[PDB]
RNA sequence: GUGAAGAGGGAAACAACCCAGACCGCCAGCUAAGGUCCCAAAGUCAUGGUUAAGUGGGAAACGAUGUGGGAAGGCCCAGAC
RNA sequence: GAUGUCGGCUCAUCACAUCCUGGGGCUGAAGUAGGUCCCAAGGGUGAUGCUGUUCGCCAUUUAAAGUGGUACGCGAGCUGG
RNA sequence: GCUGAAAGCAUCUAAGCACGAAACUUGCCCCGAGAUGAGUUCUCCCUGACCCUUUAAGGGUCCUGAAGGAACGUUGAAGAC
């Protein structure tokens, strides 16, 4: 079933009457406007393309402006597609807002995790460090061996090594929906979601449930 | 089931059958007479 | 081969359709049909059918015998059908038919419900008997086997679903 | 005098459409390969592609003898150490029916850039509808 | 006997195995061992059989109503299995 | 005219003759728990006292604490008992 | 296991039809059209003259310079560059 695009506002807590503190992520879900509808006849698959937010009129290019003008919607900060289930049907220019999640109870949140930059093996793959003392010679956080010997004679593909960590697409599944707040355009989910404050999140009803 | 290189009729109620390229002995009187060759 | 030598007698009220390989039988019990092997002659004659091999088909006699047996079972199918009887042995074991579904209480923590296929009907005279009726011999045998598989007769008291005409052959543990 | 050599800029190639339903896989792939390479032309030259374009229809109806429909296995390795993957002939026909014909013919074609250029002229389809009516392919019986 | 101190062709590759001993040139022909569906030159050759495991294309004692050929015995229309 | 050795550490990867979990046949299988064989390599598969030890013996765990190959895997990665 | 002959019977198998495991293919997550087999969809931009010969997917001059991009600057929960 289709999802929505919001932004990570931050984290807080919700106190319940029986004395439980729920950590929540606050997701601001403004209305998403349908910009294009794909169908089997023309595109080969069924999907809707949406936009949300706002963009500076002098910062939106002529091709994007023309694409928005065909749908008759104001420019947003991006475009996202959601695949369409069999029963679902939408029309170009229609607004979809946060009460879509009114009775969902579990969501799948996708965002871009924070970038850690170039990371060593100890941090990136939880490699164990070698001895801090007892003779160790300049080899305290180094990876150790990386292969066997003549018989393979190479390093195997997929070897765990140091490199870029984070700053990639991550999904967290089956988060409790704590509060759907229609007139505030707020979605409150329980737990942490990928990304930094102010980043874009895609929220979808949980597929595993 | 006995899995053996040499399967044989252990009594008179035992029957040698070939099921999908496997010589098997199915007895109708004693369950511990079941054999497959392999 | 030789089983195939004996023709199958068509009684009155049952008629035969032959389309080369696919043959259909009609009767008071319903529609039975199958496609025979590519290596068997079937020929309707005076109230009988006869079976024989083609040419250039090795082991056409074995297929002829198989086809003869299947057709003979079809004939007894559309007339008076076939019946299978099951017995439930063991304390608390019970059965009941609700239309197309048999409900079995076989000592599990969950109910057991079996969905009968198209041409099979069931009825329980008592709560520990099951009687199946149908035209297809293979299908009724398959249904009886499926019912038996839920709780196979165990060899120490004979408890479980079993065919009415079945010998269980229990045993003792060590002594006493 | 020197023997004739085909000139790549003056070779004339025709379009043929073959129907694969019921044909034995290898015995069809052999004829396909020899006509893709050009060995049927008297102008055959080993270093220039003088073959024809072939359209193959009904790739999922190709036939194998014996027990190969469930016993012929297609191996390939992904490049990772886990690596080795396999699919039977039935599984390949169910997933990508075109590739059984494609890899049979590719195995029967010469190796190197010319062999790949030759393979480029084979067009395999699962149905019996192709998109190359503008090329006016002639019917070929194999 | 060959290699060593011998190239060429075959055995996928493969001193020492099979065929065969390179004076030089030829965009001529016949053969050897090995081959003749495609990679890859030449039989999708002809006739008669066998095999159904991809046997062919790795492995023994031993095991089995897997089939094809002999060769001879029983039991049987007074009725055999 | 040099292919660094046992053990530890770090990092592994494959085989299956399977230690655990999964499926099944037989049992001298009532149940619980076992014995034995067949299928199965997806994942998992201890911390210590002693000793340079691998191993082993002990002490406590664990669903289990598998067997092997990889220059007795790994010193242009560490140690150097 | 069902039905079932070869082999009047038996037989899960030869024809035919059911079940059946963490293994296999999917289902879940991520990369992914340099998939040279380089795919698809939507939107935006540019519709002026002349000259030469070697004649053609030819060159050269004048006018023109779009949509976009880059560069520079202020920077970032992006980053070795």
Image (cartoon, coloured by chain):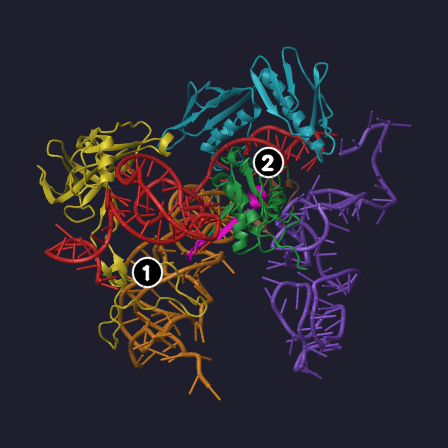
Chain colours: A yellow, B brown, C cyan, D green, E purple, F orange, G red
Question: Where are the magenta residues, as a range?
Answer: D68-83
Q: Is residue D72 magenta?
A: yes
* D44 on left or right of G72: right
Which disc, if any, is residue A160?
1
**In the foreground, D51 or C67:** D51
**Residue A177 visible at all:** yes
Classify mark 1: residues with Cα within 10 Å, few (<14), some (14-19) or many (20+): few
**Residue A3 visible at all:** no
* A89 on left or right of D47: left
**In the foreground, F12 or A80:** A80
* D109 on left or right of G62: right
**In the foreground, C13 or D94:** D94
Which disc, if any, is residue C77?
none
Q: Residue at x 58, y 41 (%)?
A: D14
Quadrant for residue A173, please give it.
top left
Callout 1: chain = A
| The residue positioned farthest toward the top in the image shown | C13
Q: Which residue is drawn at 26% across and 69% down?
A: A130
Classify mark 2: residues with Cα within 10 Å, few (<14), some (14-19) or many (20+): few
Q: At which x and y percent is residue C56?
A: 73, 34
Callout 2: chain = D
Q: At which x and y percent is residue B9?
A: 65, 45
Q: Residue at x 34, y 68 (%)?
A: A145
Above or below, B31 against D47 in this view is above
Q: Is residue A125 magenta?
A: no
**In the foreground, D100 or E53:** D100
Q: What element carries label 1?
A: loop
User: Which residue corresponds to mark 2?
Assistant: D138
* B19 on left or right of A156: right
Q: At which x and y percent is residue B3?
A: 57, 50
Quadrant for residue F53, please give it.
bottom left
């Amino acid at each position: 079933m289709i999802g929505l695009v919001g932004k990570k506002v931050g984290m807080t807590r919700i106190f319940t009457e029986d004395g439980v503190s729920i950590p929540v992520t606050v997701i601001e879900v403004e209305a998403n406007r349908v910009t294009q509808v794909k169908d089997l006849a023309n595109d080969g698959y069924r999907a809707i393309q949406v936009t949300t937010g706002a963009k500076k009129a002098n910062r939106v290019t002529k091709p994007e402006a023309g694409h928005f003008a065909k749908a008759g919607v104001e420019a947003g900060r991006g475009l996202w597609e959601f695949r369409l289930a069999e029963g679902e049907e939408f029309t170009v220019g229609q607004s979809i807002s946060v009460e879509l999640f009114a009775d969902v109870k579990k969501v799948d949140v996708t965002g871009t995790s924070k970038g850690k930059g170039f990371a060593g093996t100890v941090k990136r793959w939880n490699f164990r460090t070698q001895d801090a003392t007892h003779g160790n010679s300049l080899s305290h956080r180094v990876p150790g061996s990386i292969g066997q010997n003549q018989t393979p004679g190479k390093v195997f593909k997929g070897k765990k090594m140091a490199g870029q960590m984070g700053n990639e697409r991550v999904t967290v599944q089956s988060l409790d929906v704590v509060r759907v707040d229609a007139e505030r355009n707020l979605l409150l989910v329980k737990g942490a979601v990928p990304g930094a404050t102010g980043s874009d999140l895609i929220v979808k009803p949980a597929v595993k449930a | 089931m006995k899995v053996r290189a040499s399967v044989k009729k252990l009594c008179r109620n035992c029957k040698i059958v070939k099921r999908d390229g496997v010589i098997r002995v199915i007895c109708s009187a004693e369950p511990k007479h079941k054999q497959r060759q392999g | 081969s030789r089983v195939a030598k004996a023709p199958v007698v068509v009684p009155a009220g049952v008629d035969v359709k032959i389309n080369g390989q696919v043959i259909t039988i009609k009767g008071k019990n319903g529609e039975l049909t199958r496609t025979l092997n590519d290596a068997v002659e079937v020929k309707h004659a005076d109230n009988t059918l006869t079976f024989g091999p083609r040419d250039g088909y090795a082991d056409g006699w074995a297929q002829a015998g198989t086809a003869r047996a299947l057709l003979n079972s079809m004939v007894i199918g559309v007339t008076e059908g076939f019946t299978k009887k099951l017995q439930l042995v063991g304390v608390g074991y019970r059965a009941a038919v609700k239309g197309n579904v048999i409900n079995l209480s076989l000592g599990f923590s969950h109910p057991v419900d079996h969905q009968l296929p198209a041409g099979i009907t069931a009825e329980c005279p008592t709560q520990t008997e099951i009687v199946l009726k149908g035209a297809d011999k293979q299908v009724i045998g398959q249904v009886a086997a499926d019912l038996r598989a839920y709780r196979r007769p165990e060899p120490y008291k004979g408890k479980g679903v079993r065919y009415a005409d079945e010998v269980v052959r229990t045993k003792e543990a060590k002594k006493k | 005098m020197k023997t004739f050599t085909a000139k790549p800029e003056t070779v004339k190639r025709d379009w043929y459409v073959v129907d694969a339903t019921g044909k034995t896989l290898g015995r069809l792939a052999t004829e396909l390969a020899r006509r893709l390479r050009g060995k049927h032309k008297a102008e055959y030259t080993p270093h220039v592609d003088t073959g024809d374009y072939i359209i193959v229809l009904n790739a999922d109806k190709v036939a194998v003898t014996g027990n190969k429909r469930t016993d012929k296995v297609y191996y390939h390795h992904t490049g990772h150490i886990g690596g080795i993957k396999q699919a039977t002939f039935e599984e390949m026909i169910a997933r990508r029916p075109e590739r059984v014909i494609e890899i049979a013919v590719k195995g029967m074609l010469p190796k190197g850039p010319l062999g790949r250029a030759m393979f480029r002229k084979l067009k395999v389809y699962a149905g019996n509808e192709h998109n190359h009516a503008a090329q006016q392919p002639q019917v070929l019986d194999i």
